[PDB]
Image: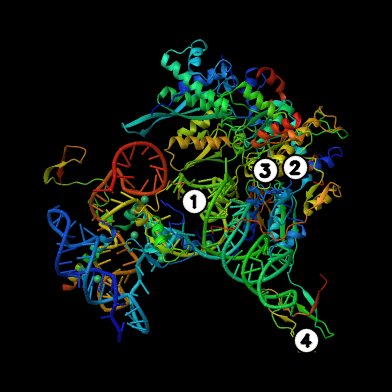
Amino acid sequence: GALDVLQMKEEDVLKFLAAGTHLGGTNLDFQMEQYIYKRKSDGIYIINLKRTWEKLLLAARAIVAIENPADVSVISSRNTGQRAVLKFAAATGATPIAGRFTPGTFTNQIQAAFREPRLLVVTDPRADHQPLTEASYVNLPTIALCNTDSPLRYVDIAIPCNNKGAHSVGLMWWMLAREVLRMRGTISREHPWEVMPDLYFYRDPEEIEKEEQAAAEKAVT
Amino acid sequence: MQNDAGEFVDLYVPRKCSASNRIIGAKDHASIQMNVAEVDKVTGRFNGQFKTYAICGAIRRMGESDDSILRLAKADGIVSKNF
Amino acid sequence: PLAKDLLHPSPEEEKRKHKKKRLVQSPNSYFMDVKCPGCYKITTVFSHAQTVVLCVGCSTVLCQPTGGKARLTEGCSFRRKQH
Amino acid sequence: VRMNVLADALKSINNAEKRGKRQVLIRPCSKVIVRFLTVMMKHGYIGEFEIIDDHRAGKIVVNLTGRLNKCGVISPRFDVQLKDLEKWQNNLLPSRQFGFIVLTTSAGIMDHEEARRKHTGGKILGFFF
Amino acid sequence: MGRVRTKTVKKAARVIIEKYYTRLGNDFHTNKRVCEEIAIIPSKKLRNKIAGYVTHLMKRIQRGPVRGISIKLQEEERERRDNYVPEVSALDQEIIEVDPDTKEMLKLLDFGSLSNLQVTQPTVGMNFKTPRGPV
Amino acid sequence: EWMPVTKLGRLVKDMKIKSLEEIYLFSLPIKESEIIDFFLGASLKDEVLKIMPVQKQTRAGQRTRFKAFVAIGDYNGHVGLGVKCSKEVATAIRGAIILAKLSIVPVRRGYWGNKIGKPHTVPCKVTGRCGSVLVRLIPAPRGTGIVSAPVPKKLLMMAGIDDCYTSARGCTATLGNFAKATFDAISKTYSYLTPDLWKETVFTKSPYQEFTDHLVKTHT
Amino acid sequence: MRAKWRKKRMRRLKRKRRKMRQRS
Amino acid sequence: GKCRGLRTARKLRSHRRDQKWHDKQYKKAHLGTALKANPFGGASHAKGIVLEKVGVEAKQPNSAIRKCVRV
Amino acid sequence: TKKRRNNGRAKKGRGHVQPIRCTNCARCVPKDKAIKKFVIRNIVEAAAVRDISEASVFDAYVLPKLYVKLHYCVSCAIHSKVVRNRSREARKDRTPPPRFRP
RNA sequence: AGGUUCGAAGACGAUCAGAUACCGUCGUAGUUCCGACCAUAAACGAUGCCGACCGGCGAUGCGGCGGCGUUAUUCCCAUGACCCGCCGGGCAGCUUCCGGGAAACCAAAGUCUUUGGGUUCCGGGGGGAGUAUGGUUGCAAAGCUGAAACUUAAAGGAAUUGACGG
Ligand SMILES: [Mg+2]
Ligand SMILES: [Mg+2]
Ligand SMILES: [Mg+2]
Ligand SMILES: [Mg+2]
Ligand SMILES: [Mg+2]
Ligand SMILES: [Zn+2]
């Protein structure tokens, strides 16, 4: 996105800094080197937020180019992102796959679990290498949410934000959903989106089993 | 194709990779052809027409697919020059 | 990266690369003016000098040859020649 | 040691072409290399190439257009008469519809079709198709 | 020893649990009395073995979300997933502890000089990396 | 009676895709043999190349399965070679026929020189490699026919090539590898880039996006 | 046999042959 | 590898003619001792006198008395 | 067939490595080829620590450790079960087995 | 010269159907040093040398260069010991659909039918045979060069299944 309306806003910058999504790993992939700003004294690589925004806009243009919203598939094998891809598919009408991605989903045409999408979006290339390689048998262009040390073997629209922080993953997924909705005739580009970014955040079970009762005690008293 | 008489004697013309300028084979299932939907200048909304990029299987197996897509989008104007 | 610009490398990788393996060879050394305290004259000394440089007006050593660079004696001022 | 500068340059160009690179650097430049690249570029197999000129033998950065299959060399510069140019032409070229064989002639460094046009032979240099 | 159940009983027990979770209970005899009309079991021994596994699986269900599908368990899961967005976001922090290098990155991005950012003092020592090898 | 489970197969069945070259343009894999017999109906000739009895030693002696090599292709520029091994000869034959139908590749025909009419020979010398068998297909003038060993001769004949010089190296007695190397050589006639293909390719709509509404209505 | 022991046997035989030839 | 110089023809022909002695066909045909050992002496046929009639036992998997003549 | 890339020894940029005698059978084994085990064992058995502590003249006496380095030819190493045959893929990892601290 | 240990030969004791061996005891030549021979090893990376190109990563040894800092003395910088990088040459290692190969595997065993950077040595089915003979070196043992008659349809290499394993 080269336009002035298609620019990162201060609210977006604040979300990005609060959720993290710029503190990469200590390892740098040579094909991810073009997204890094600088390496800290901690060894943590600092990812350029503008390059991340540009790649996210490129991914949004790739996604909205498909007439059937069901033809794009979102996969998160790791738990930190399954809720994000579920909410993303619910908002955008995509087809989600969470948890164990069974082999032969895109290639073995016999089982009913077989499906052939027109776009692949991946939370993490290391966690989701199995849908990555299978996408190479069916002519499937791929988007992935790649970190500084993510391999880029079968990735096409690699977004350099993060894959480790749950807050960062929820934020990047919510941001992608908001962008692909604003590109289509869904959001009016003026008021902020009514969907809170916390909705996409993965929560560890010891929060689910204590937060609801803490909130119940606060409400009842 | 295109013998002396002029007609194109070849039953198809294959696509060439938009990065490596390589012929995408008939059985090269690793190849892709994605569409990047450009928006209008004023509201940033999809306007129906788009632009198309094709990558051969060799490039997007050695890993250089993302760089090629970014370069083509930069050249065509999708990505701003200040990237 | 399939499209590294070999014609116009930025000065950072130009300076990190080996002197022979640069686009054009450039020596890593330089010439320096050396001020010995208590003396007015100025001696032009090679940055990688292999010999002990002495002031012709004072029996003082200015640099001690080492493996890579002549280590200047303490208290001695130095500056560059035309970058 | 290096005994054929042109062979090294052609091998570097071929390797960079095979690896999908957009630009190749060949370290030892020479008049023969510049003329060979001129023939290749005028036939459209390569793009513009720029000569980096140091006070030693210069370097060349060539813009690869991706439409090159092979740019090999014939190392012993065999004398090629016009009577035996056809055997060379059907031993080194993939077909008769495309491919060029560059040989250094008395009239200069030029491909085989120009040599046959002006009726002269010479010493073989290399082939590119 | 050798009391292990087979696929025939386990799959049928899971199916009749996920079809008739409301009617089933923790009593073995009640379950073996509902089986004859909610299912067709050719043998009495097979029927009561299925009922026993149903009792065990419903004990496991009431003590935890077994992989067997359950509409009440799934609606609880749905309520616990697509809700509990906190009334205040987790990303609207008043102050953000920012790296000076990231501050320079934001400055070059042109989004520097923001009142919500607090510049951290960068650490000194460069002592990351685990020690190499054993010992 | 053919019920397809594929977007591509569904588009083929309901008259949405007209030519096999339309599929070949986008490199879409064919995953069911009932796609092409709709296209190459009654024109796909069939020939069984060899029946070889592979064996696997077990506790109670050895058991034998029959590996069938089937090469098919209309004599117009399409060819395919399938290899299937099964217990029964007929089952292996049918499986190899289906696989040869699946691995149907297009063949590029060129001219030896002085392009006059329909092309007759390979556009340039192509090399196929499989195991230790190396097969090279050299362009030949009109009327020379296919000069080669019989096993590649029939495969080149059914591929639409009229004239071709052939040079083979290695253990050509290995009929499976020998046929597969020639098939690989035939396949990469388009994988070779030639100056008449140097024009910048124009991109058309993929059938998946061109017929996505009809796919949604029909291919549920 | 082991190749080394065939070598040793051949060396013994060669010495015997040399001795017999020298005896003439 | 092999030499490829413009004036290496002497070494190439020398190495070819030196290495040509290492295949059985050329050594047999050009050494001359195989001709000496051949009873026919380079002839297609020969005439002889039957000294005896002998039977030759067949090889191991077969079993027959091959009827030969000592000539 | 070449079973191991390193030929089962650590000699990389050397011509000759001095031999050592196997602690079990006194076989001349190259030093970089022999299996080395550095056992650090209590000089008394874990069953006898209490009795020695009771019969000690000192109150807080720290019992000595025993430091013995063992070298084995691969024959004695395999026969003594310190090393075991591994699958073709499982031969490639060099990480020692865990100490089983818990 | 010297000879402590070990230990060909040898002696004895065991084991065994036999046991000229494996095990044990003893023990010569030798193993040690100096001088003179010999020139052979699975002398191996079973992989010629020089040169160019073609992936990534983390280390390691040497030299040099640049940097927060900790440490040694001292008052500070030098200079050592660490920490983080860069460059050059090495021993290597991990990963890779670069590519190759029959495969094992190899970033060289790649850049090879799209066959040509320069050059050296060398193989032509298995045996006979590294034998005979000749020549030559050596005190000797032996080293180097090295056939033929005849015989044979296989011998071999890598991998798969099975069987078997003191
Ligand atoms: Mg073995
Ligand atoms: Mg050695
Ligand atoms: Mg003794
Ligand atoms: Mg050479
Ligand atoms: Mg032989
Ligand atoms: Zn031992």
Q: CA distance from mark 2 to mark 1?
A: 38 Å
Q: Quadrant of residue A123?
A: top right
Nearer to us of marks 2 and 1 is 1
Does the Cβ of the disc 4 residue fall within 8 Å of ligand 4?
no
**Left or right of F25, for residue C26:** right
Rendered location of residue D31, percent (x, y):
70, 60
Q: Residues within 10 Å of mark 2 (few under 14, many from 20)?
A: many
Q: Chain of mark 1?
A: I
Residue on which the image places disc 4: C55
Name the kind of residue labelled 3 in the image. Lys
Asked if marks 1 and 4 touch (Cβ < 8 Å), the reply is no
| Image quadrant in which the N terminus of chain D is located | bottom right
Letter of the chain that mark 3 sits on in the rendering? A
Q: Name the secondary structure under disc 3.
A: loop
Front in this rendered view, residue A56 or I23 = I23
Do badges 2 and 1 share one subunit? Answer: no
Q: Marks 2 and 4, Cα distance to the nearest angstrom?
A: 63 Å
